[PDB]
Amino acid sequence: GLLKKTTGLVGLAVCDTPHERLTILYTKTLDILKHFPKHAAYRKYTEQITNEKLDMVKAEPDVKKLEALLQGGEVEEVILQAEKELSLARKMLKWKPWEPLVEEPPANQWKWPI
Amino acid sequence: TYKYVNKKEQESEVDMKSATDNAARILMWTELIRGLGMTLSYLFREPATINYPFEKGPLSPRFRGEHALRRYPSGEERCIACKLCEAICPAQAITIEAEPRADGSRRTTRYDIDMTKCIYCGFCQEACPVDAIVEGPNFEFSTETHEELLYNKEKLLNNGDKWEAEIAANIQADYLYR
Amino acid sequence: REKMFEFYERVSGARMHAAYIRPGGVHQDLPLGLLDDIYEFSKNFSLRIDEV
Amino acid sequence: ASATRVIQKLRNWASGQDLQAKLQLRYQEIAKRTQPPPKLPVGPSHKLSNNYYCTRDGRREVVPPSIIMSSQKALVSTEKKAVTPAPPMKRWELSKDQPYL
Amino acid sequence: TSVKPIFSRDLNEAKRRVRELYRAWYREVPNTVHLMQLDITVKQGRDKVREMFMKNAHVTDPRVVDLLVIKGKMELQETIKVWKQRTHVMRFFHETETPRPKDFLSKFYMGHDP
Amino acid sequence: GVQVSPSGEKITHTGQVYDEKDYRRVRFVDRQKEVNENFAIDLIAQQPVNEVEHRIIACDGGGGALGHPKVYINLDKETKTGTCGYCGLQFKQHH
Amino acid sequence: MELVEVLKRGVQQVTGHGGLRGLLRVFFRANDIRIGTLVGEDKYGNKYY
Amino acid sequence: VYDQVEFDVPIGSRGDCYDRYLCRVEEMRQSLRIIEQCLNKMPPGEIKVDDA
Amino acid sequence: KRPTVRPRSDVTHKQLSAFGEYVAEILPKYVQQVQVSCLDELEICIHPDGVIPTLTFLRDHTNAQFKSLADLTAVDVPTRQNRFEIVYNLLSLRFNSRIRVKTYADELTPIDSIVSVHIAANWYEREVWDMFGVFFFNHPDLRRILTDYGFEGHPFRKDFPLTGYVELRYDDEVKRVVAEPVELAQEFRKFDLNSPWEAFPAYRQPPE
Amino acid sequence: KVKQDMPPPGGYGPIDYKRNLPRRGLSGYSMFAVGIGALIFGYW
Ligand code: SF4
Ligand code: SF4
Ligand SMILES: [Zn+2]
């Protein structure tokens, strides 16, 4: 299909090679996820999300039909989101949110009405 | 459904005709001339100005203006000092005191409205069970001092006696919507 | 705008701070003849937009 | 309304519009300032029977929030699938009335 | 009695920040008197700074001292930027206020307030 | 109705009037004390008593939905009239 | 031709207020010389048109 | 009752003041389109919840 | 179908409940409570340490995408030892959903600023500092925003009086506006309105 | 019977709302031809 003239969003430029770029970002995300503990839920769910999207990119070579499958807007918004998930995974590796609750609140902290 | 307000970018080739039309538009200020045409067309329109104060802006019977205290057709005050208007007043603009009148009647001895606290919301006249306190139609009561806008009961009853003929007719026109 | 302030004042008695929409609905029903006057305003307004 | 036919032509030509068909000043087309009295209808709870308030009391149907997980009193705990807060929003369709200005 | 610190781990570290803020306020008074055209001496401005600091001399909690310094830096910032006007700076001097007498008899004559 | 105190000040229908030695009388100097002259207590007392055929009469104050909440007045006591607690009208039973 | 109709309505407005003094009175009191139907007069002397 | 009326959402392309001015002008035109439907589809009945 | 009662669907409640479990399983280090109201609004209650990780996760994660901070505010509850409840209201355009994240603070425990996650939070955090006196760590530029210059106290605290402590007037002797202790010609009249009869048995608190 | 404020039977007439700016004026050629003809005549 013919390359897009604009994405429709100010500041978001057209990607010439969206299939390649998505493959790079999703593959990079799955690499950093192997550094998480196996039991961490963020790893398991993000692996499911990413593999599902990676298989769509492998399946569909048409950009327009790929956008229909991904359901994340223009393919350039999908690429942007893919970069955001990768950036998050690097942060989650240092935050370690999978660890037990750091502290309980006071007993009536969340009791409403008082 | 959505529409584009400024996506007319179906870029096309330019003929001599369209290039000259574009050239004429730039060099002869044609769209600026259309602006002058519009303001010229207003010059010859009848202006919308009314001749205040000999003419007035239209109003409706629901208009919320200067407050008044009303009476029954006998001359007895309608207000029975229930204080519903005072309780609901979102500005606490109403201050009321009451006691048994000499004939045993439940009547007010103080009924004040701070017109500089009041927000002219009409909640008092909705809340009144006896149509005693109303916002009348008058809107021309600007004063030269702050103190003149602290209305007491005598002032509010005089507004009622002053404006009842128009107030009664406005209530007759709207009460079936209330 | 001055004509639309009249619709406000005709439903609520106030040109601006109507206090007309309340939890549960609206304070009062439309006066008879208001829809016709809103229609008369509405059918000319797009020309006013065109001039601007 | 009272413009002469010459001035009407002048202002119609100058504006590029037919101004006489949509005058901004109001004449006799508007409602009369006195109207017949209304007679408003009553709502669906104006019934003499089968109308017990406890069968139509919305406030008494409100309940406290459902506790999904609580570090205090409610433990939250095949591969469980990932979920979104809601399904993805469908793309808007381009207007058929007038897609482009 | 185990609490999170804000900035200072002990009252000694907090006293260090207090002295820094005091220096900053001390140096600012002559520039403020000059730029705002205040009808006071520089000495009178620095005595007022001193009196405001000693209004809190009794505070021992390092966290409260941290927050007093944070607020003192804000007040300094709106003074240097001339966000405060003359009315605002002169408010510190209470020049139209008749002070309440401190003895029992004077308060007894005036009214019922302790 | 409106009377005057010894100082000359009009007395209101609520019985208000400043003392002669009240400084607050200064506020009316070269101005005026506003006093409504139609005392409701005097006007309601001018109304005739209504004679009715029953022992319970309903008063809504006249004008239907423009009056006051409809109340029922007992007329069994023959030594006095039943007075409406809202509008002050009086009723008496015929026999 | 239609101008002549307009000027004649101006003559009616200018001569329809009770002579010169009546035209000056309304013109300088109200800044308006339109003629309308008299709807009434109240007890204070206000005239409604 | 916004899910019962037809109208279009004006969308900008450049994200600048001129596009936002065009969006607001067109939103007024779409408001007239909604008003027309409100006038014709105005239903009968009460105007506040029948729940005293 | 009952014309005066608000209609309800179970679909949004189920969807929001499931996403609440999802968020709690991913962030157990911080999540203290998850609940979905009968108005179908999801609230995640977190320990204050989790503010930046939690809100970063909700912005950037592909199944969340809460990219728009609708508002950020506080609630003062004097009976709690951590009297300030910090509320983040977030919007996801991708999934057309809203979520609320709540943490708590006291007078001497600052919260982390989330300006690095949402630049929108900048003025909101200034508003929370101004109105409630909650300090934010690592805020670029924290200072009053609504109150007057040199204003003392945090007026949205429950124990700050409605009319405050100082009022303003012009004084002709000094030729400027001056601040003086508040004195009112008419005191605000306090109304005791609560009925002594219980309104909502569904919220009756244990008799203890 | 109940009397309320309602639309007339059949509804109101259709309302214009789309932009309507007239197309007007001469071609580019006619304007340039008139302008150049004024110049040449004046030069002469
Ligand atoms: S109009 Fe509103 S603010 Fe004014 S006195 Fe009545 S209830 Fe109070
Ligand atoms: S004016 Fe009406 S609401 Fe107010 S105290 Fe009198 S009777 Fe009650
Ligand atoms: Zn009665």
Image (cartoon, coloured by chain):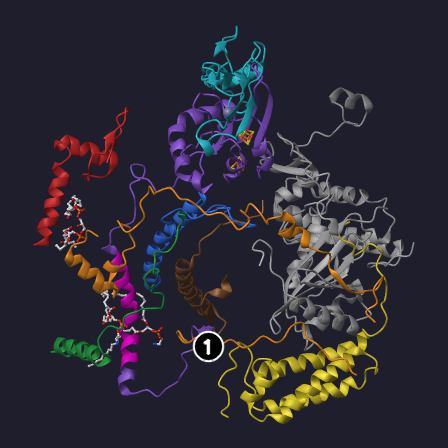
Q: Residue at x 39, y 85 (%)?
A: B11
Q: Nearer the viewer, residue F83 or D22?
A: F83
Quadrant of the snapshot with the N terminus of chain E = bottom right
Tell me which chain the residue with mark 1 is part of: D
Residue for badge 1:
D94
**Disc 1 on helix, strand or loop?**
loop
Please count the marks in the image.
1
Q: Position of residue G11 (x, y in %)?
A: 11, 42
Q: Position of residue J13 (x, y in %)?
A: 32, 62
Residue nearest the observer in this picture, A29 or B144: A29
Please name the amino acid that badge 1 sits on. Answer: Leu
Q: Residue at x 25, y 36 (%)?
A: G30
Where is residue I143? Give x, y as percent: 68, 55
As displayed, is residue B84 above or below residue J17?
Answer: above
Q: Is residue H37 left or right of residue B36?
A: right
Chain in purple (letter): B
Tell me the quarter of the picture where residue J21 sits: bottom left
Q: Colour of chain F?
A: cyan
What's the colour of chain A in the image? Answer: yellow
What is the span of residues highlighted in magenta in the rendered image? B21-42
Residue found at x 71% / y 82%: A86
H47 left or right, relative to D60: left
Whether residue A113 can be seen here: no
> Is residue J13 in the magenta section?
no
**Quick check: is B31 in the magenta stretch?**
yes
Colour representing chain J: green
- The picture's colour for chain G is red
Q: Is residue I203 left or right of residue I186?
A: right
Task: Judge whether E77 appears above or below F55 on screen.
Answer: below
**Chain C shade in the render:** blue
Q: Is residue B159 above or below residue B36?
A: above
